[PDB]
Length: 461
Ligand code: HEM
Ligand SMILES: OC[C@H]1O[C@H](O[C@H]2[C@H](O)[C@@H](O)[C@H](OCCCCCC3CCCCC3)O[C@@H]2CO)[C@H](O)[C@@H](O)[C@@H]1O
Ligand SMILES: *C(=O)Cc1cc2ccccc2c2ccccc12
Image (tube, rainbow, N blue to C red; front, side, top):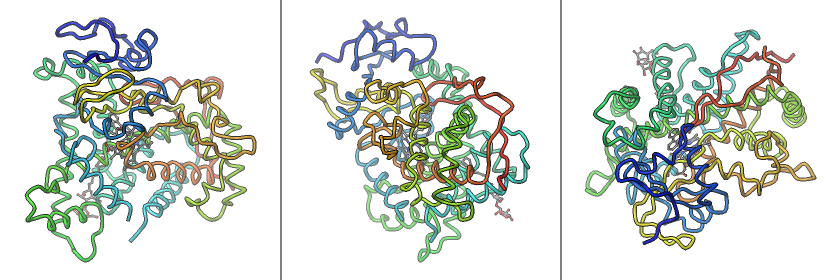
C-alpha cells in the first residue's frame, strides 16, 4: 500500500477542486510545489502517479524500465485505437508490434533520401511563392505527413492535391481538439461525458475518415502486391500476415494493421510539423542565431549540394540549435501516459499494477539543474567551451526507456534536413519585429500548439 503523497480525493470528482483552470500541466506543476517530485493525483475516480524533474523520470523510465514500460489510455482517442496499434498496445502485442515497426523501417530508397526528396520538393514550392507572406502551417504538415505517406503508402502527394489537403485538414484539426481544455475535461469524466456531444465525437469522425482511407489503401496494396518486392510498410505487414496464417497467437492482423498505420501518422506528423513551425518562430525572434546557422551551413555543406545526414556530425552549432528548439518547444509537456506493468516499488512508495504514470517532460526539459536559464532560448545549453555538442541529461523530448519515441531517428533526420535545406536556399523575414514576437502557445495540453504566424522565404543568390 501507500501511494505517493497527494491531496484528499472525492469519491467521484477526484481532485477536481485541487486543479488549476489553466490546464492539466499547470495543475501537475502546481501540485509539485506542495507535494514534491513524485505524487498521486486522482483524475476522477482513478489514481495517476505524476513524475516531475529529470532525476525521478530517469529513476522510473530508465532504472526500472520494464516496470514503467506500460502504456496508459487517453480518453479522447481510445475509442479509435482500443489497445490496438503500436502506440497503445501492451504486453506481448506492443512488444511484437514495436519490434516489427523498428525492424521494418530500419531497412529501395532510404528514409534519408525520401526526406531529402521532400526537402527538394519543398524548396521548389517555396521558390514559387517568390518571397510573399505565408503561414507555413499547411506546408509543414504536408512535408511531415508526406514522409509517413512515403513509409506507409509507398509514395507522396503534391502540395495542392485537394483530397490530400482535405484529409490533412481534418486529421490536423484533430490535434487542435485533442489539446483543447474541453478534451482535458473529457480525460477526467469520460465515464459520464461520453453520452453527450463534445470534442470527442469530432475527433472520432476525423480519425475514422482516415482509418477508412487507410483501409482502402491496404486493399489497393493487397491487390497490387508483389511478394518479391514489398514497396512499403503495408506490403511488409501483409507479407507478415501471410507468414503468420497458421499461428493463432499472431498479432499481425487487420485491426493492428489499420491502427499501426494511423499510429505512425498520429504520432509521426504533428509534433514534427509543430517543432519545425516553432523552430522558425524562434529563428525569426533571433536573427543572430539564424545567421550562425546559415554561416555554419555555408562553411560545411556549401550552396550547391543538398544537406545530408552525415553533415550533422560536422555541424555542432546547428545541432545545438535544434536541441534547444526541441527543449524550449516542449511539445509533449506531461508526456504520454505510462502504466506500471506490475506492483512497483518506487522511491519508498509502492505503485499498484496497472496504475497510470505521468512523466512530466516539461519539468525535465526546463530542469534548472541542467539549464542555466530554462525559460530563455540559448543554443549554448548544448555547447561546450570548444563549440562542440554537449549531451545534457535533462534533454528528453522523446521521453526515455522501453517506450522511447519509436521514430526518434526519423524525427531528428527530418528536423535537421528540413531546417538546413530551407536555410541553405532561403533567408527569413516577418512583418513582426523580433522583439515583438510572442512565443506563448495557442493551446497547451498533451500537445503544445505554437501560435500561427506569417513568414517570408527569400531566395539566396
Ligand atoms: C518532433 C519529433 C517527435 C517527438 C518530439 C516525439 C515525441 C514522442 C514522445 C514524447 C513519445 C512518448 C514516449 C513515451 O511513452 O514516453 C513518443 C512516442 C512514439 N512516437 Fe514520437 N515524437 C516525434 C516524432 C515521431 C516520428 C517521426 C515517429 C515515426 C514516424 C514517431 C513515432 C512514435 C511512436 C510509434 C511512439 C510510441 C512508441 C511506444 O509506445 O512504444 N514519433 N514520441
Ligand atoms: O494519378 C491519378 C490516379 O491516382 C489516383 O490516386 C488518388 C487516390 O484517390 C487517393 O489515394 C489520393 O487521396 C489521398 C488523400 C491523402 C490521404 C493521406 C492523409 C492520411 C493521414 C493524414 C494526412 C495525410 O489521391 C490520389 C491522387 O494522386 C487513383 O488511383 C486514380 O483514380 C487516378 O487515376
Ligand atoms: C506529437 O507527436 C504529438 C503527439 C504524439 C504522441 C505520440 C504517442 C502517443 C500520443 C501522442 C500524442 C497524443 C496527444 C496529442 C499529441 C500527441
